[PDB]
Amino acid sequence: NLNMDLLYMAAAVMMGLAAIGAAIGIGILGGKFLEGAARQPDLIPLLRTQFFIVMGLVDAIPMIAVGLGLYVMFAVA
Amino acid sequence: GNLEYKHPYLEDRDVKRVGYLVVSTDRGLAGGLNINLFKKLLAEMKTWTDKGVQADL
C-alpha cells in the first residue's frame, strides 16, 4: 500500500545525504592528512593517530543517519 | 633535514671541468704568501688536467 512507497523514499533521502556528508568530510580531512604526510614523512604514525581522532568525530551524525535509514528500511518498511 | 630538496648545488655530478676562485693581495712585500698559494694551486690544477678535465680561474 501507500506506506512502503514513501518510507523507502525517506530512507533513500536520509542515506543519500549521509553519504554526501561523510564522503566529503573525510575527503577533505584525508587530503590534508596526505599533504601533511608528504610534507613530513616519519610523522605518518602520529598524523594518522590524529587523523583518526578527527575522523571519529566527522562520521557521527552521518552514521546515526545511516543507522536510522536502515531502521526505517528493514524495521518499519 | 627531515625534508629535502633536489637543488643542483647539493649533488655530486660528474666532474668534467673545475673552476677556482683565487684570492691574492694587491700589494707586494708580503713575503712568500702569494707564491706558496699559487704553487699549491698549480699542483692541484696539474693533477686535474692530467685526468683530462679542464680548469678555470
Image (cartoon, coloured by chain):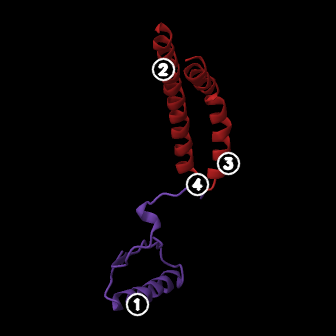
Chain colours: A red, B purple
Residue under the image location 61 percent in, 27 percent down: A63
Which residue in the protein does label 2 denote? Answer: A12
Q: Residues within 10 Å of mark 1 (few under 14, many from 20)?
A: few
Q: Quadrant of residue B14?
A: bottom left
Q: Distance between the residues labelled 3 and 2?
A: 38 Å
Q: Nearer the viewer, mark 2 or mark 1?
A: 2
Q: Which of marks 4 and 2 is in front?
A: 2
Specify the label residue A41 is tagged with.
Answer: 4
Q: Which chain carries label 2?
A: A
Q: Earlier in the sequence, mark 4 or mark 2?
A: 2
Q: Which of marks 3 and 2 is nearer the N terminus?
A: 2
Element at label 3: helix
Which residue in the protein does label 1 denote? Answer: B47
Q: How far apart are marks 4 and 3 (CA)?
A: 10 Å
Which residue in the protein does label 3 denote? Answer: A46
Residue B41 coordinates in the image, percent (x, y): 44, 84
Q: How far apart are marks 1 and 4 (CA)?
A: 43 Å
Amino acid found under the numbered disc labelled 3: Leu
Q: How far apart are marks 2 and 1 (CA)?
A: 81 Å
Amino acid found under the numbered disc labelled 2: Ala
Element at label 1: helix
Specify the label residue B38 is tagged with.
Answer: none
Amino acid found under the numbered disc labelled 4: Pro
Q: Quadrant of residue A47?
A: top right
Amino acid found under the numbered disc labelled 1: Thr
Q: Which of marks 1 and 4 is in front?
A: 4
Whether labels 4 and 3 belong to a single chain: the reply is yes
Element at label 2: helix
Whether labels 3 and 2 belong to a single chain: the reply is yes
Nearer to the camera, A69 or B35: A69
Nearer to the camera, A40 or A27: A27
Whether labels 1 and 4 belong to a single chain: the reply is no
